[PDB]
Amino acid sequence: VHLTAEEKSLVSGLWGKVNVDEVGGEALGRLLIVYPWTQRFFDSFGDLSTPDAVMSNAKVKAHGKKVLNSFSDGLKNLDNLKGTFAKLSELHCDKLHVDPENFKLLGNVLVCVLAHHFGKEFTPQVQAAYQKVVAGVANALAHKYH
Amino acid sequence: VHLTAEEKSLVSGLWGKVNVDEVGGEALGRLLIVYPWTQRFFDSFGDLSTPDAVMSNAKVKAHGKKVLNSFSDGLKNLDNLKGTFAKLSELHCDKLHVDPENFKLLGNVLVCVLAHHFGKEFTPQVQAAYQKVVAGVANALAHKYH
Amino acid sequence: VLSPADKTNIKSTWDKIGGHAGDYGGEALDRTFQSFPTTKTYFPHFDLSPGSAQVKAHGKKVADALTTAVAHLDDLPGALSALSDLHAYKLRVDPVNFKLLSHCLLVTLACHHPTEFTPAVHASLDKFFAAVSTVLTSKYR
Amino acid sequence: VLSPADKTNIKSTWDKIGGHAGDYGGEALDRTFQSFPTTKTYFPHFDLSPGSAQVKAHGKKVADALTTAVAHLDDLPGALSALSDLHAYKLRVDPVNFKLLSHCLLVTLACHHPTEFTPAVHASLDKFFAAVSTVLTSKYR
Ligand code: HEM
Ligand code: HEM
Ligand code: HEM
Ligand code: HEM
Image (cartoon, rainbow over all chains, first blue to last red):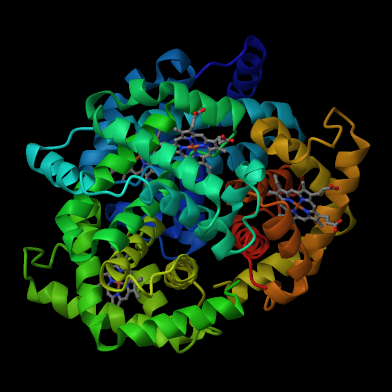
């Protein structure tokens, strides 16, 4: 995905302030609550039966941190997202059978979490830039499905 | 898109029997009726206010024939769908602003029309083969959006 | 959201198919499994080979559920509560799969009833299947 | 489809935002136009520049419509019939755009009310916006 210099700065400025221990787990947790069919893929994660169980789930937090780091990899490789996520695209398709629509959902949930954390700092301009990023990541993870 | 020799034969066998004057207009007509927001893109086509008006619309029939021929181009170029539809992808994105989801819808409507026309001849095996074709065409037309 | 005309179209079409509904349920499943192989991962316990007794029997159940829905178009959440519990709470079926099955139900009906499958009926049936899908994928305890 | 808990979450959250709703409607539109530029093609008659009076005024109307919806969660088709006529019959808005605006409404609420925007409330609001979207994109005369 192509971001202008301005868009890149808006993204990077916010991303450096992100709590890397919490944001990913909160994004994954919200995905599992707002779009509860996504829980199907996480049988080995234990209790997901209530919002509180999801948000206190240690494995969700730990896996969320890995997902967030993977987003960080995308931010460092915006001009080669397909190459960065090809192995992960293979995993989600062939082994996990995750429908590609869900990648868009997680991207938008992450945006909601960023908004939640940063408040007024998460301006419409900052959001617009992040939407290009998450759409790029979702497209890259869906590439090996086609 | 990769079709096996068997899948290619199932597709070609049916396609040779298709009424090229009617099927495309029926597919487009059904798209405009089943998913009525698609009518927004066709202001110059005249009356679309009732199912009967849509199905008797001369411009819908004529444009449908062009759409069907474009599908025929895809069938002749299955290994280079992106190259075949790149100019059309540009048109639908930059000029027309058609959301990519609608390409999947038209593909599935065409499948419904084929089923309607061929009945029991449109077997589950023939359908499966055609689903690969229409998904390929929809993906190819969506390529310049990314 | 379903129009008065939609409800008339749904009831009339469903009555015309009559006792063939069960068979069509089986065919729609077969079409779904063949066309969209990922849907098969919800049925690992099923023999999914040609002529499967399990698929035929399950098709009857799906058809019967849709017949129940036709009788309760104004209160699908109430009428299909148990099926929502199954598909939303226990099976946790991705909504995408409902779109795939709904499409194959339309295909099956078009294959068997061309006179009935008018553009208007096509439109009403798609809305019908979508309404049912929303109920079965919703958690409304 | 909306749960009893959903309805409680929607009402409580909407009451907490109170008179700020109108402003949030404007912000959500701004977010939608900036993030998803294709949505702007529905508003060629609008000045869409920063500080637009048209956007602010329209945001108030959108917010008021959602307030009406909150009061009629058990009969959205009845309560929003005129808006369905506008968005489905006249404007013929692609359903995709409703998903985009709904997302930006969630973002706007998260930006302003972090205490209120719990995962459970987030879930209920998404269902709320989806329910409204279905009504406005449906033709049910
Ligand atoms: C937003 C895009 C996504 C990114 C960047 C992402 C990233 C990752 C990463 C880095 C892993 C670990 C790979 C490994 O170490 O083997 C993973 C695994 C996994 N992902 Fe995702 N993911 C995304 C979307 C999704 C979605 C939407 C779902 C389900 C709806 C999903 C389900 C899973 C599952 C079930 C695993 C394996 C977990 C385990 O059992 O250890 N992913 N993903
Ligand atoms: C199934 C994939 C599709 C194919 C293969 C296809 C094919 C075509 C072709 C061949 C043309 C004529 C190009 C030219 O001669 O300039 C065209 C134009 C057009 N298409 Fe499509 N199309 C598809 C999907 C769609 C969809 C889903 C929509 C709207 C929802 C749409 C809306 C239009 C419009 C408005 C025009 C211009 C019509 C005019 O004013 O002359 N297309 N398309
Ligand atoms: C048209 C929408 C659907 C209807 C009306 C429907 C209806 C039903 C019915 C009546 C049952 C049997 C319940 C019982 O015996 O108590 C059932 C079970 C089941 N459904 Fe669905 N269903 C639909 C969509 C789906 C989809 C899209 C999937 C996933 C691809 C799915 C997966 C399953 C599975 C795995 C079972 C259990 C089968 C068994 O163990 O025998 N359903 N459904
Ligand atoms: C949350 C869902 C939505 C709600 C509650 C809503 C509500 C409204 C309301 C209350 C009006 C004013 C009606 C009147 O004055 O009689 C309106 C008009 C309008 N809506 Fe929406 N709307 C929604 C979604 C959308 C979307 C997604 C679009 C397209 C991107 C859209 C496009 C328009 C347009 C172009 C107008 C006319 C504006 C004008 O000329 O002043 N709406 N809507």
